[PDB]
Length: 304
Length: 304
Ligand SMILES: COC(=O)Nc1sc(C)nc1-c1ccccc1
Ligand SMILES: COC(=O)Nc1sc(C)nc1-c1ccccc1
Image 1: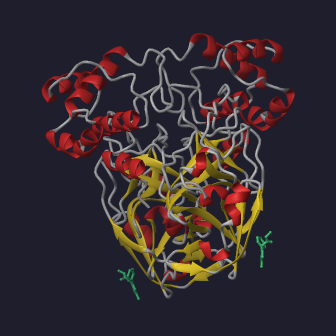
Image 2: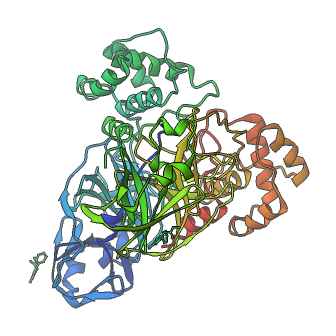
Image 3: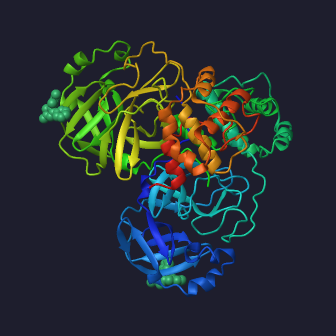
C-alpha cells in the first residue's frame, strides 16, 4: 500500500551522461553508441542567446572545439552535425554502458522521469509531466541544460525530453532527442509566454482510482454524470476535455475498483465545485495530475 | 529555478539489489562486498508472522536454503547469521558494483531516497522522510521488503533504511542496516499502532525558504515571533517544537534570502492560523515537511 510520486530507476541513464564544453559554455550531453547529443545552444555565449544565428555560429566551430568528458576521461570528437535544436557529436568510442533505447516524442499529459545533471554529473531524479501548454515544471539551475527525460519499459529506455530553456515565468521548455521543441518554444532568450496550464483530467481520474485502491475513499459520492455534463464542468475549471479514448484508457482501473469511469467523473465534478474542505487525498490538498493511468497500474502492480 | 521532490540518482544502489528466496518467501537483499543483507522474516511463512520465534525458525535453515540471485546469476551462500532483525548472508563473491558505503541510523525528520524493488529488480525511486513517530509513508507492495533507503554524499552511499513491515494503517516500518527497527515496531503481524504523525517544523521552514528563492512569496508578512510564542502555535497544530539547533541549521537559508528565521516562523504561524485560502506554495496546497534544510541548499545549489 501507499502511493508516491515515483521516478524510474536512473542507473541506465546515469551511464549515458557526459559533460560538453564549447568555449566558456558547459552543459550536459547524452552519450548513446558513438554519438553525444546536446543542446545546440552549447555554442552560444549568453550574449549570443538574445538573437542567435546557429548556422553562422556553428561555422566557427570545429570538432576539437567540442570538449566531451565522460567521468574524468576525454572523448575524441570525429564529427558534428546540427539536427533541429540538438547537436550530434560523433565520438570515436561507443558508450559501453549504452542501454537498449528509443527516441520517442511524447504527447501532453504523458509523464516521464528527469535526471537533473550538472557538468555531466547526476544530482537528482524526479517525475514530470508534459503540460498541456508544452512546458514542464522542473527543477533546473544554470548548467542543467542537456539533462534528459525518459521512461523505462523493462530494459529499454525511451528518451523523450532534453532540457533547453527556462521561460521568464520559471517553467521549462525543451526538445525531443531529434531536437524538435515541445510546443512553440525556441532556443532564443526572448519573450515566450506559456498558454493556459490546464489540468490533465484523465490523470486526475487515474489518481482518484489510485486513492480508492490505497484506501482514501471519502470523496466517493452517490452521483454519476455524462461526458458532456462533466466536460461543461471541466471547461469552467480549466481541465482538459475528457474523451471516450480517456474513458477507454481508464477501463482497467474501473474494472479493478468496480467504480464506473462516469461515477468517478461525478466524484471529480463534486471535488471541483466543492473543493477539498481542508481534507487530503493520498497526502495531497489538491487534485494531482502527474500520474497517468499507466503509472497508476504500474505502481499499483509492482512492475520492474 | 523550480523546486521538486527529488530522489538521489539510484544507479549505485540498483547495482546492489538481489533476490533472496527462503522456501516460498521471496524478497529483496542488499549485496555489499561479500554480504547480502535482508529482512530476517524471509524465513517466515505468513502463518509464522503471527507469532514468529526467529531463533527457532532459523535453526531449521541451512546456507543452501537461502537462494540469492543477482540478475540471472546465482550466488553461493557460505554462511549466514542473524543481527537484530536482519540476516547477513555471506556469499563467495564480492559484489563488483559495491559503491563506497556506510550504514547510518537516521533521526526523525531526516529524508532519504527509497529504491522500491520486487524480486531483486528496481521498479522506482522516491523521496521519504523518517516521520516523528518512526514510520515512513512509502509505496510498498508484497515482495518489496528488503528495498532500501539511502542518501548519497558525492560517491558514498549512506544506507539508512531497509523495508520490513506495513502497519494495518498502511504506513511503513523498517530497520537500519544493523537490523534495529526505527521506533517501537517489531517484525510480527500484530497490533502496532503509530503515534501522532507530527509535522517536521524545521523542514516546513526550509521549504518556505525554497519557495521564496524560487519566487513564491505571497505568504511573507509584516510580523515576527519568538521561539516560545511560535512553539505555543506549533503545539496546537501538532508541529514539532522548534529549537535553537533548528534555527542554527536554517542560518544559511536565512543569510541567502535575508529573511530572519523568526520572521519566517511568523509567516508559518499565520499560515497555520489562517490556512492557504485556496492558494499554493511550490505547487502544494499544504505545508510540505519532507525537505530538510540540507535538501533545500543542495537542490538550490545543484550539488552532484
Ligand atoms: C553533417 O556533418 C557530419 O555528418 N559530420 C560528420 S564527419 C564524420 C566522420 N562523422 C560525422 C557525423 C556522423 C554522425 C553524426 C554526426 C556527425
Ligand atoms: C554466526 O554465523 C556465522 O558467522 N556464519 C558464518 S560461517 C562463514 C564461513 N561465514 C559466516 C558469516 C560471516 C559473516 C556474516 C555472516 C556469516
